[PDB]
Image: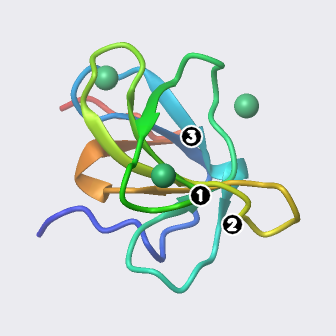
Amino acid sequence: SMEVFQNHFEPGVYVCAKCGYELFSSRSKYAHSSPWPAFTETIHADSVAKRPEHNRSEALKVSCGKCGNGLGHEFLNDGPKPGQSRFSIFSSSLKFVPKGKETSA
Ligand SMILES: [Fe+3]
Ligand code: NA
Ligand code: NA
């Protein structure tokens, strides 16, 4: 079965599924009504690269800052507290690294 992180809230870090760069902490994740996992901030300042999303106001496209793999969107001023973003990310673009449990293949 494919990765679906919408309702997933375990302790760990979501990394880029393509290159492994650290993207989002479990700390930053919050429950939302949309089909995609929602986060307020990235782990590193260069975790994501941003580009305009021309056909939607208050929205940017986001990709991995290291390898360029497409991640989803940053919705400006759409987060849980005023002025926070909602990073709405494809689960297929993420791999979850659980605290304590990064076991061998
Ligand atoms: Fe990457
Ligand atoms: Na951060
Ligand atoms: Na936009």
Q: Residues within 10 Å of mark 1 (few under 14, many from 20)?
A: some
Q: Is residue 58 above or below residue 67?
A: below
Note whether ligand 2 is within 8 Å of mark 3: no
Contact between marks 2 and 1 (CB within 8 A): the answer is yes
Tell me the element at label 3. strand
Tell me the element at label 1. loop
Q: Is residue 97 above or below residue 76?
A: above
Circle 1 is placed at which residue position? 58
> What kind of residue is marked 3?
Phe
Q: Is residue 103 toward the left or the right of residue 84 in the image?
A: left
State the mark number for residue 78: 2
> What kind of residue is marked 1?
Glu
Camera-near label (3 vs 2) is 2
Camera-near label (2 vs 1) is 1
Circle 3 is placed at which residue position? 24
Q: Residues within 10 Å of mark 2 (few under 14, many from 20)?
A: some
Tell me the element at label 2. loop
- The spot of residue 1 in percent (x, y) is 11, 69
